[PDB]
Amino acid sequence: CPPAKVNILAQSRPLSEWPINLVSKGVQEYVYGLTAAEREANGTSRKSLDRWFARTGVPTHGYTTVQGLNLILRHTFNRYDGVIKKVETRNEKRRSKATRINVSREADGLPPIEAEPEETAFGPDGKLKERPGINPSIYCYQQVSPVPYNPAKHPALPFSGVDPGAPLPLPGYVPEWQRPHLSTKNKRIRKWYARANWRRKPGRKSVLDEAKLKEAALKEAIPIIVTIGKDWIVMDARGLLRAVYWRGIAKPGLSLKELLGFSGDPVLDPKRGIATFTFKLG
DNA sequence: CTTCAGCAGCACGTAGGGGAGAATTGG
RNA sequence: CUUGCUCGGUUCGCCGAGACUCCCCUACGUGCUGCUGAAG
DNA sequence: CCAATTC
Image (cartoon, rainbow, N blue to C red):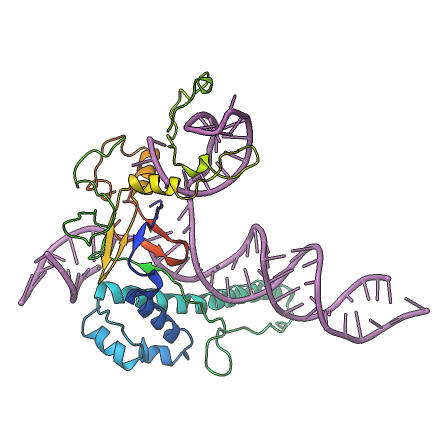
């Protein structure tokens, strides 16, 4: 299941202010640090995750979605136990080392020697020692998936979305002295607005018109709008188009129905202004 | 003006926890 | 092969050669900064 | 349709 990247183009308000991000971070800040006998009492239903949000003092910000709540609760409590799992596995290896030295101990016939003490992940106050930090990932789920852009349905915005089904489209003077060795083989076709062509390096003298490349990248945008609640993330499927193009899956035959068909559960990373997409099973 | 000594890191490997859906279905 | 990353050519118009299992977290290191205690 | 259920 190889990954792919999409650069977020448009959004209403920053990802970190989304109810999904807020509720995730709250759940993690509450769970993270809890005595081993507290996580038992506080450790898939509308009813279950409507008393869990009352027994625990984790407020919900207007986000009651089973597909949107269970995820956080599945990851958090698996991390809290992988932290204990690191200590437990190291202790298991320590006990294996004790067994290894004991084997030779019976062969020598001497009484067993003293063994080093073990460790835990909790200190004396009952709280966790290696407290895991807050993952900022805003995971997306089935009912809120990458949909193409249709200006009739989605909110007005300067963009231009192609029809669900149509084979997607397949300055730049290439001057005469540039044509004795133009690449006859198959490779990428960048464009005039590509930023690899305008980066500031000493052998270059026309560097980085600030808005021109950005505008000509946005003109030909393939937008996809994941909409969670009243918030929307308008994406750029070109990064997804490249991945299927260079990985030998579709050769100039796809639309914004088959492209997205190649997982509708993206992982959004708010800090980088990026989106991550998975593939199918093969 | 030197060895070492123990914490931290702008920086780097490691090193090991975790994560990366889609099929009914009711109302 | 439309975004995006790395590195090169230039007449400054884009051209060429590539990477593409990624994100978070805990800790620790080696070179350099910082606080100290030994020896003339 | 679309937010809830399985596994």
